[PDB]
Image (tube, coloured by chain):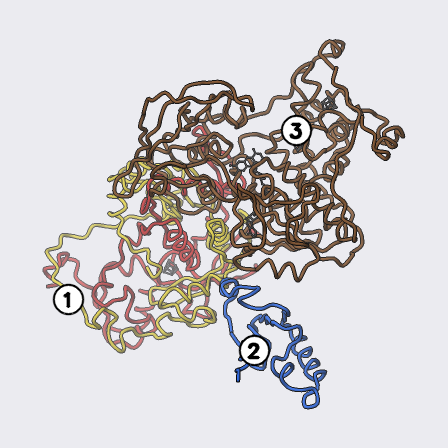
Chain colours: A yellow, B red, C brown, D blue
Amino acid sequence: VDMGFVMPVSAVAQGIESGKIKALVVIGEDPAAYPQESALLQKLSFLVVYDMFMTKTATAADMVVPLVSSAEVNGTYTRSDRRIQAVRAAIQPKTGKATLQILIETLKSLGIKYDTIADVRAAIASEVSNYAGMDAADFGTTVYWPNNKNVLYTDGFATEGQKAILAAVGDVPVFVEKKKYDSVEMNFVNGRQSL
Amino acid sequence: MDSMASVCGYCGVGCNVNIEYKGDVVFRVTPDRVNDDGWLCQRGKFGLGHANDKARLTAPVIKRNGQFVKVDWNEANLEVVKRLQAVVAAYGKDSIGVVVSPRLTNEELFLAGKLADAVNTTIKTSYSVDGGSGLGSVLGYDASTNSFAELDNSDFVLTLGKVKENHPVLDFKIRLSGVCSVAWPQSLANTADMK
Amino acid sequence: DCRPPCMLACPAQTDCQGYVGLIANGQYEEALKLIKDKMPIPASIGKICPHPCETACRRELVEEPISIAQLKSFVAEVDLNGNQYQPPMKPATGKKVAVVGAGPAGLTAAYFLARDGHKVVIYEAMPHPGGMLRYGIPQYRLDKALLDAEVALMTKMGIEIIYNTKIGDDVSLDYLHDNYDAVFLGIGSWQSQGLRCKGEDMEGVLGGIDFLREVTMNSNITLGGKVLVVGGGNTAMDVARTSKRLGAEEVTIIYRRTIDEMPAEKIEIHEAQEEGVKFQLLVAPVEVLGENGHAKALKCEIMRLGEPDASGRRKPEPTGETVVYEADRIIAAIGQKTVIGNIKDIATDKSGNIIVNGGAFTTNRDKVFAGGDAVTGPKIAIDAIAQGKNAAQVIDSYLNGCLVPHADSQYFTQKDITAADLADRAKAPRVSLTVEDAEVRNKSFMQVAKTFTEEEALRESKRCLECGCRDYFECQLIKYIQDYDVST
Amino acid sequence: VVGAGPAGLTAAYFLARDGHKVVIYEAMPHPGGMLRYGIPQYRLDKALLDAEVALMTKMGIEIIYNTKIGDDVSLDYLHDNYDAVFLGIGSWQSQGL
Ligand SMILES: Cc1cc2nc3c(=O)[nH]c(=O)nc-3n(C[C@H](O)[C@H](O)[C@H](O)COP(=O)(O)OP(=O)(O)OC[C@H]3O[C@@H](n4cnc5c(N)ncnc54)[C@H](O)[C@@H]3O)c2cc1C
Ligand code: SF4
Ligand code: SF4
Ligand code: SF4
């Protein structure tokens, strides 16, 4: 959410079916397990899948690039309560290159120069608004992204006019259960049934 | 067994874990009793077993004549960059959508955003995130206004949804805290009752 | 024959018979040691050269000639994958030479000057070295990783290359004149000729060189459905096939003379025809039609075949018939022209090329030398390599206090050899090149041809006729003929 | 840093003391500025200044002499190739009568 991946999926579906979107890049997801999304993906022109397994989506792609698991990656995860926790790699990447390395070489080809994870963290600190201070954050301790504060809106809300926006909501039916799209989650669910 | 301190990669509670491994094989996962409360759920405890799977991919493959051909990393990088550039050239701006999974670290998500910026597109999305929780339009930030560490001192906790079934370590913490927790009734599924 | 026809036809005078025979004896390292006496980048040159040496091979009098360029590329790649060769250098003399531009001429001059003990610095105006071999030759013909590896090997010899530095705009030439003992200008020709017609400034019309450079730097380009390429040289072919690989559904090439009079290589034309670019023939530009600043049509006249010129190609004659062609992009690839830029106090001719004293490579300004496409205009890469090597030799002689011009040598040659003189030789088919099918070529940028294997290289190299004299390196008659200036 | 006068030398010293990499472009064959070409020898010994500048150079600061910005190297070159530029050119024009 904090890096801007907040566009709704219905826009992607409409842009696929309106002919405006011609290529898709899927990183770690499996939308093709469901028939309607598979039919939508079949109307593409070029599809890349980054995934650990040869899943249903990667079979129908034009190019598949392997990924490493959470035991082989160095980085950070942002908790639900805005806490940034370090993720440390236990074993060396069994495919040869980490995901960060793959993205770094691709951006190197496209003309953006990064060397290691320190440069990426400095860029995150200097470009993402609320992660200012990630460069010397020392993720071995408690780090929260809004000015290292546990509580939000202590001095007013963060809207345009510093006021809460109240809008009327209509009638709402019964909740519709969400689906699982991450390949690791569905893999765990299917592997539960093996025993 | 050698031990490495990481965090769980399955939901947003983000429990700290110790991965116990010997060489290139992960053998077990234990809770981190020093830096956290030391609780885990089934997904955190028994979920890293995909790191030892033999069906994981090892090298990138490019489709020719309907069959996947193993290629080097440099050839894969060239192919994906040139095909993306060809799509951009043939169909102009906003023809490429970048679908990611929320399991990636902060640096990989930032680099995927940089790649989306560099290929002249604004369509960055996720099927899991699917537009956020809707709290952003009201208060400005799509984030929790309080941390988990403040569940100990509250005198009343109202739970909406299946908090126990989906994020059970949070339920363990709430039960051990002893505060008065009241669940929203199930027979109130429409928002007219919220009105 | 003091030297074989194949070596004499090569612009750089590379000893083709020597290293072909050394391949036939299984000595690949010695073959590369022979090749690297004339150029520092043998794999790329073998990959892209139009091989004038192969035309003059006497094996043509029996069957197809020896695939000399493929053998050169095979040996260069075998040494690059194995133990990289570094030729010996003389002890340092303390002289400083600055080379402007990292193209084939600049790279060759720096190589052969650093091999004489001098300290050479290359100033390059682009982020990567190679010149038009990098920003003009497409990836599917010349792999850029090969060129990068070769330039890294050259840099390991002690040559400093400074990128993103343009002479005249960022560093003045007076700075190099004051701070160095010699300067060699290998700037090359980097300006695209216009359509030379009415409405050539309309938006939607772009040069071939700039389009190819934008393709190489992985920038954001716009092509659309229909692309019209104007021109008939190698630039038109490369632009057409690059646009075919870049998602254009149809590409049209427009020229004024016959297929038989195209200046491009026949192999490249046939490959382009197989890939899917349609040729539109006997047509010259008339008027560019566009609306609201956007060009969508190209108006042209239809010509007819006429008398051959002095260069052996039939002249076009107008017919008075007009035809308009729909397009989404129009690319002008008529040719390249030399631009001097902001460098001042350098004399230039009527066509823009640098004027030099013939045989000594000296401009009007003292301590400043020139060569390559900056002098000869647009030509093939081996010509630039030869000019760079000769200018490096001349600069090295000039640094010693006595300037000596470059002069050619006299050899005995035989011109009465016919097929009836080679009726006793056995016939062996030439080694075919394995070319990837037209399915994968149209969509990808990967290589279209594979390098020779060891067995194929031995089979091809064991087919030479050994036309040269075996006693040349110890014959005394030719020694005295060269020494006493006697014409042969 | 453009110019090796007291201002340029001090800026380079206190920037190299903070971990950055500093390059000094000087338009004269020797460093010092008006302390060298304006102060006479009988008041300031030039060997003393040369020894101090050598001490500063031992810290890892590269000084490029005979390079005039604007005439030999454009300022756009320094703008493109460096993270900061400090102009310490000083006043070097004589007033007329
Ligand atoms: C479409 C196309 C097809 C070709 N096909 C072939 C082929 O089939 N066979 C073949 O052998 N060759 C081919 N060539 C290459 C060409 O024929 C020669 O290789 C050319 O002579 C390159 O040599 P050069 O000395 O001109 O180097 P250049 O490529 O001209 O090198 C000049 C270098 O100097 C740099 N420079 C320019 N101005 C300045 C300045 N002011 N200050 C500093 N640096 C500067 C340039 O950026 C470049 O790096 C092709 C080229 C093109 C564009
Ligand atoms: S509750 Fe379970 S799945 Fe969620 S973070 Fe904790 S261990 Fe992982
Ligand atoms: S550079 Fe060209 S002419 Fe010279 S030997 Fe090689 S292929 Fe023949
Ligand atoms: S047969 Fe051999 S020696 Fe004779 S021209 Fe051909 S390559 Fe040269």
Of marks 2 and 3, the one in the foreground? 2
Residue A138, given in percent of the width and then of the height, sits at 48, 71
Whether labels 2 and 3 belong to a single chain: the reply is: no
Task: Indicate the secondary structure of the residue bearing disc 3.
Answer: loop
- Cβ atoms at labels 2 and 1 below 8 Å apart: no
Mark drawn on residue A166: 1
**Number of other residues with Cα within 10 Å of mark 1, as a class: few under 14, some 14 to 19, many 20 or more:** few
Read off the chain for label 3: C
Residue wearing tag 2: D8
**In terms of depth relative to the viewer, which is nearer, A71 or A165?**
A165
When the figure is inspected, residue C446 is found, relative to residue C154, above or below; the finding is above
Could you tell me how many numbered marks the image carries?
3
Q: Residue furthest right?
A: C476
Residue drawn at (69%, 40%) of the image: C39
User: Residue C90: x percent and y percent?
Assistant: 80, 51
Disc 1 residue type? Leu
Quarter holding the C terminus of chain C is: top right
C-alpha distance separating marks 3 and 1: 74 Å
How far, Cα to Cα, is label 2 from label 1?
A: 58 Å
Compared to residue B77, the image places residue B41 above or below, namely below
> Pointer 2 and pointer 3: residues touching (CB < 8 Å)?
no
Q: Is residue C392 visible?
A: yes
| Three-letter amino acid code at the position of disc 3 | Thr
Q: Secondary structure at mark 1?
A: loop
